[PDB]
Image (tube, coloured by chain):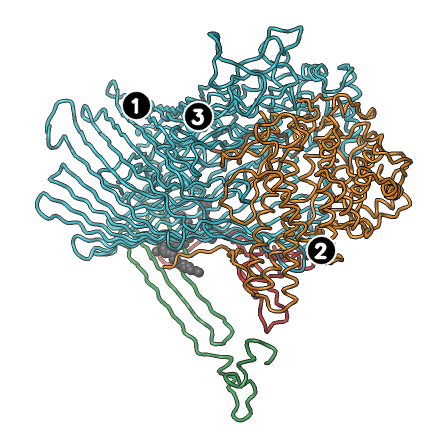
Chain colours: A brown, B red, C green, D cyan, E orange
Amino acid sequence: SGATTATTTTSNS
Amino acid sequence: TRTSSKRMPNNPYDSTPLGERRERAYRDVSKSFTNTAEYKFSIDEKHDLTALMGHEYIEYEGDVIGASSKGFESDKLMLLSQGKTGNSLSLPEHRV
Amino acid sequence: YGNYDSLKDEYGKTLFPVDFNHDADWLKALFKTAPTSQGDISFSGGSQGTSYYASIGYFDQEGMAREPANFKRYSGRLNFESRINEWLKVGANLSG
Amino acid sequence: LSTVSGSVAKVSSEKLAEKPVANIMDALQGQVAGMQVMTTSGDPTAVASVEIHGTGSLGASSAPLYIVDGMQTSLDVVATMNPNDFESMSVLKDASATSIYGARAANGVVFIQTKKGKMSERGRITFNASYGISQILNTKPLDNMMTGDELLDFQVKAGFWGNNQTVQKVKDMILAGAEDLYGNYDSLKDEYGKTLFPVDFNHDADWLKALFKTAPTSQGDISFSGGSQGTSYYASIGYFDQEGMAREPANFKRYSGRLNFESRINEWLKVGANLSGAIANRRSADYFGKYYMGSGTFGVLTMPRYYNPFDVNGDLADVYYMYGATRPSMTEPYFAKMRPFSSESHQANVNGFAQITPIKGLTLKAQAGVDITNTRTSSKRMPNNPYDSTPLGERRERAYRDVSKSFTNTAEYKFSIDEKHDLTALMGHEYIEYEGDVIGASSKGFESDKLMLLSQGKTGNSLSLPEHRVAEYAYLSFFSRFNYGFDKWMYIDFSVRNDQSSRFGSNNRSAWFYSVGGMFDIYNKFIQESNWLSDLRLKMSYGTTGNSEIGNYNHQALVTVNNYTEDAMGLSISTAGNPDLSWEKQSQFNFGLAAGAFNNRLSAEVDFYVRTTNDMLIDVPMPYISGFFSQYQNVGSMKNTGVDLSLKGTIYQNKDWNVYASANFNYNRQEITKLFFGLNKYMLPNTGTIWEIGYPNSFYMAEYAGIDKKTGKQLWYVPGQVDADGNKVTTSQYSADLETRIDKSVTPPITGGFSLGASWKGLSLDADFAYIVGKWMINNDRYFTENGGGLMQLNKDKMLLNAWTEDNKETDVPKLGQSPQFDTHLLENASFLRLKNLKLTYVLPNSLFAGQNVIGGARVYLMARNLLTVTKYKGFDPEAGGNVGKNQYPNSKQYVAGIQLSF
Amino acid sequence: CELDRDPEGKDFQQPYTSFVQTKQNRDGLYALLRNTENPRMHFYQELQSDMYCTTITDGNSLAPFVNWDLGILNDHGRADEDEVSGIAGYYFVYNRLNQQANAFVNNTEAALQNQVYKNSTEIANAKSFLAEGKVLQALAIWRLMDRFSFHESVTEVNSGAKDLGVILLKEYNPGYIGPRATKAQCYDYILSRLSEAIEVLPENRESVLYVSRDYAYALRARIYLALGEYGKAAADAKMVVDKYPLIGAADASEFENIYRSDANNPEIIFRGFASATLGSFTATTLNGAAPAGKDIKYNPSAVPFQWVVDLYENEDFRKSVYIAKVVKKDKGYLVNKFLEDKAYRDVQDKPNLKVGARYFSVAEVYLILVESALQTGDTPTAEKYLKALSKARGAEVSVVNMEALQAERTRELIGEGSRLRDMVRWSIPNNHDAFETQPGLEGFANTTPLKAQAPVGFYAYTWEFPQRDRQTNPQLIKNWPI
Ligand SMILES: CCCCCCCCOCCOCCOCCOCCO
């Protein structure tokens, strides 16, 4: 758990 | 075991036009182990003896889950999660 | 019978719910004659040390009362017993 | 099984037997040519991802058909089968071989055959046992991160804690107000300072020891095999247990059983059965793949090193501190103790067949089977927790059920129309069915941990609504296959099948496929005797197959319940629908050449394939103005062209030695030839990829140049522009018009492996290598450890100390207040070569078991899995990925030592 | 074999043949509206103004919007089967609402023309339902035009996009790609929907949970004010301003007890249904709240500046309801408007911080009426309503001179996301680098400069079209030059 750190790239393939 | 009861909506000769649904799942598991040593022999020609020793373990475990919902208005849209909330909610069932 | 759209045009022509001349049959309206089917095929045999017994079967019994009370099973069996070598013998009974 | 003119690669039983994982297809990495196995997590319950001859469709699945003994199975069901029961594994990667399988057999078929008892005077009893440990494979990427003192000085200088702030003020009056939080809790009130230092600026905390561990693995099985002159049996009972190497618990455990039985009743009947079952407990670490604070490998990289999760004894505490928090943060062994989770799944697969030969020639075979899974899982949220948001607990119980039936009835008539003309005719029927449901219930408001039945919750506004999900499908199929063989050297095969599925509309569901294959034995007609050459066959095939793996109800236009009040119901529109959804057609041409050599000491195979996907099933991205996310449609095309070659050898030396080798290789060139809305290219947003007509699935990002040494900004190349003689033109303003399609493919083109094997008088050594060349991945964790713009509370890489300032003006990392982009400086070269397993076994010699007749053999082996990797990827693992390396559960590294008693 | 497998819990899309089918699809339209027009989607255009300062708790979620990070704000947000958030989520939910209102309106129009309803009361109810759907089409188009189209005081744009609107669909088909409409076409479409729907809906409010004539007047006044026409805005706000009384409280706790409860708040023109079990949600972004036993503990990702706190006098009732001094247990202020509602509680003793959606309140009708009366040259009406609103709120205004109006509108609508539109409409630049932070919160709230300067006429006040559009149809002209 915890706080979510943003700026991910969404995985496709 | 897996059990499903239903009560259908939009029925004219009923007291409510709303339907109900209930789904239960049963499980029971039994386990058993028995180990045994037997020795039969004869001391003389006129004597026979048979000795038996043994161990046995029996175990049982049972379990029931079950859930209900109500307030349906169509025969197609009657999954257990598409019911009405509020006063049409109930506590589930659980026994061990 | 006049308040319901399924019965307001059926009274007097096909539905006579109150009949005083000749009385009704309430054993035909609550109990019936009900069928029962069975069927089973089994293979036994055996050889030098080994023996087996396999079977598959079906059972259907419907209750004689109008409110339904059936029982239906599809079942299978495999018993098996082998002599591995001079001191050991193994076996299994499987059923579902 | 297959045709003579097919491309079939068989894997023996010695590649499947002693493996320390529950992922059986992971044992096949670098073993079949053209089959690319990649497993993207080291979770004990994770499963592999197979692609034979490249990816085949953009929207549908590319997984093969997995078949165990006739019935097609999922890979989670095969996860519950003991692999010491498997006799062989044959991969039918062709169009003349996958002609009697038809669900998604355009993608290849993996056929697994179980052992049957070789009949003799005495049956055989084997007893295997094994134990081993599992670790993390790469602890190198955290040798570059900052320490505690450097991180606090970097944060103080970078203005994160405020203007005009000394390292001592932040160190004392800011961060060591962890006394105020710990003083409010009765269990930590009198423990702070004595045996609990949650903020420690002298030493540095070890977060790899807090978040990962060394796990055990054990297995064992007893197996009997026998048979008389007519019948035969193979029975096996076993046990497998694998623990996960992270502190967030994940485990796989199963107790299996198998009885294969086969009997010749009389001179026209032969019956048989393959009964199997298991009891399995799964649990997966279900927070990996996302970014949280102190979770995963992101947590070992980015937690500040002046935060201590331990005691003064060196053991792990129950909580830790992070500044600004309002409650303590639970560690992993304590969060796994207040949130329990159990799963128990019972599995039974019963197959059976009856084979009848009335006359000489034809052979009527009937086969039927059922697979039944009953899963029952439970989870809690334990009450009376001091470090929670509420003192009340919850409990959720779910019950899953899957049932799959199949029937297959064939009739084959084989005859000889002359002396030297052989024919064979086969026709058949196949019906596959599935239904599954999930029921679920919940309860909240418990106050004691013994009164936690589901019927004992609060009964007001604490009640909730149950869960229910139903799915089903069905396939009907007819087929026929004819074979012809000339004199012994020319073979032709023809095949026609008809496939219908429930996943398509009522007037679009049926399709017709065909196949033509041919083999020519050049050695037995043309050069019938030679000194060095020993076999030479030439095979050639063209076929058409179909793909239908998309999901059950995707062509209907639907409407669901969206309630507004608690009085009446409401109806919203769910999907758009597609009334003319149909199959996806794939045509494949294959041309192969197999050759032998010096009394079959050397052998080789060369295959060339072209594969074409027409009318492909794309989950097309509907634009946002429609109100739907996506829609499955029959638009687009694709093509895969390639070559794969294999060669086996024997290089041995003396009377006792026996040295052999093998190798594989496969190059594969993808090409998209038609997209969906009349488009020439489609850029997938927030993936970093593109689909463009004429090129494979490539990457799509701007090209990072460097920094401007006069200003300190980040610079990117403006695409397609060169100034006077110089170099290319750069710019310091990031625009979306700077993005270029890179010539770097998402799916890796080159795939292979090799193997070495030596032996001696009993002692043997084996080594298998597997390589992937042509792989690139976006490292997402280097967005978080290599930026001075945002997320300044995390631990950073050591290069950010040597940053650009007006004083320090000959660096190469940028100025501080700048966010990084997802450009070419985050694409890492993730190609690898891995030593898969290294086995050293020693069969005990036959002289010791001379007089004792109860033990007839013994065998001891040592084994090490995943112990070497050659990479340039700086990210804990190159294989865990698929265009983006997120917070990943890396692959394990096992050391296993087992025994086998064949007594 | 029959291979026909049909889903469970799902029926087919059919034309309307009954009156209960029209009622069911109307209730579905309102339950879709509740998950679109809720305060969670208007937090992005609230943080982007010059009132917020990110704390050290921030995990780069709110930091693109506060510090104006145009490298992230270009392609921002998700809309798929996992998550719906961001600019792309804001675009998707209002396009979904517009399309589903189109399907409802066209199906009930065809059912009215085919004469499938029995009585005359069913015809009257079906016509009222049709007007209630026309209002929701107007709201969806206006809220897309609000964020994805330029105000007329803009300097540099992508060439050809200064007088463009959004893609305008007026009938339900999901297979349509096309170019952008102009601003005049979209505004005549919005105002035609509203003026056709006022003439059918009845004079008095049927229910607070459904669209009335009061809400159509309030929405039309809001659109006319944000358009720039003050006479029609005052004329529309005058018809609804005197039917809804303000909250009559004597201290801050009475104002908290009447304001926070949806069922007893006497100045709500329109709101969504919410219960403890159906219709409630937590909006804990601006305050960062978390329950703990029986009380609440806060860990905010962004806190207001000092000039925002200094707008409120010490005896104001909104200085303990709208913003509260609860950061670091007593040290600083946060925006505490969407805290909780005590009716939507599992156990009455323990908080769960659940609220419901409110669509319009009468304290914005007052501000529209005062601003329009001040701009059209009418001084007694502006005083007559500004003194009333500010005296009911706790501290009365002395002089009314459009500095008091700007201050009172900034004080009254905080958290609702109306400040960016106001500072565009009032020619107010950013000046985020010039403001000071709260002095009691140092170490927690610190100074971060903007990553992009935003003067008057900057392009980045309006958002860029999401990148599923501009990829699926290339006849869409984008907004920004970069
Ligand atoms: C003619 C075929 C009849 C088969 C029906 C029997 C089905 C019962 O099996 C249920 C599944 O359980 C699997 C049994 O596990 C194998 C245990 O045997 C190993 C002991 O030697």
Residue D417 rendering spot, x and y as whole percentages:
10, 48
Q: Of the residues shown, which amino acid type is indicated by label 2?
A: Thr
Q: Quadrant of residue D28?
A: top left
**Which residue is the site of mark 1?**
D661
**Which residue is the site of mark 3?**
D864
Chain where mark 2 sits: D
**Which residue is the site of mark 2?**
D459
Question: Considering only vertical position in the picture, is D688 above or below E183?
Answer: above
Mark 1 and mark 2 lie on one chain; the one further toward the N terminus is 2
Q: Of the residues shown, which amino acid type is indicated by label 3?
A: Ala
Q: Looking at the image, can residue D136 be seen?
A: yes
Q: Of the residues shown, which amino acid type is indicated by label 1?
A: Ala
The image's mark for residue E479 is: none
Q: Nearer the viewer, mark 1 or mark 3?
A: 1
Residue E457 rendering spot, x and y as whole percentages:
68, 27
Q: CA distance from mark 1 to mark 3?
A: 19 Å
Chain where mark 3 sits: D
Q: CA distance from mark 1 to mark 2?
A: 70 Å
Q: CA distance from mark 3 to mark 2?
A: 56 Å
Q: Is residue D796 left or right of residue E234?
A: left
